Image (cartoon, rainbow, N blue to C red; front, top):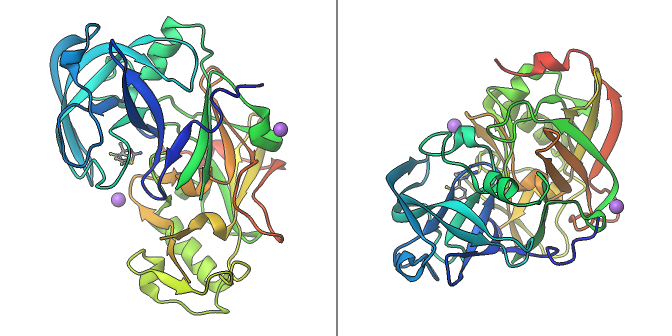
Length: 371
Ligand SMILES: C[C@@]1(c2ccc(F)cc2F)CCSC(N)=N1
Ligand code: NA
Ligand code: NA
């Protein structure tokens, strides 16, 4: 209900992610940690890498314990490798607890840290199934819930534009949203996987087989900036957005995120761009609800210059900061569901605003999931 201590506890820079202040070891070492719902490892820089403001100095900690095991984590972009261990962790602007969590001390990395960023680690908030090296390395939130009375739930209000937000650990803060929370089931506990059952570009359906919206999955990810769509869905959506926005012309490289587009300050054509609606599977048979985003969310500022923050993916749909910045999101792990409500801080205009509406009647929603 009321968690004032944790309100406004997230910071960042546009495109550089959202981070929370954390402490590791005894005596406490303060580090800024990127909040990521799309991964399950608690990894922190442990060496004097030049881009880092600070790093975890194990030698200074009495409570540190070596697991005598390493981990090599490759990505499409980045890569990091580290040494596994456990130590005492706390979240200053979080609950008043201390937990013994697994920590991957990063000893080598490539394209992982950002030059100019104010974070030194990553807090993977997803499930054990996608943990590295394997599902036996218990994620932080699982340790937090197992060792304390903190309820198995956390919520994220990502505000956007120097960026801010809130991570309410163990509860919900009703001051962070307007209207009602609508819940979608977590299909499987690995990533925060959900099912998209319909897509509308300015009230008009894309009329695709809903199985295509979730090929091979759809996930809620605070660590990705964009709304990432499967190629087929992306082609369809772009063709539809391009058509809805043919009042002003743009280079074809722009829709492909290869070129920026620029206009005048105080006069950016918002109304020439359509709203995007995703219909998510509801809690009840044949019942869905829809979430609506504004061009304010998918036209990312980089006079003014913007980026088309909707892109193709071969890993499925990724409901990144583009989606999350319009809503207050509840990761209700206890009830295996994700809640969406209109954010009290989302960026809109006098005309249109983000919306969470329901219920709707959608038949065969289970057939939208990929097997
Ligand atoms: C772990 C990862 C990540 C995020 C931000 C960053 F800056 C570095 C990263 F490696 C992989 C890329 S998508 C994702 N959700 N999380
Ligand atoms: Na409210
Ligand atoms: Na891909």
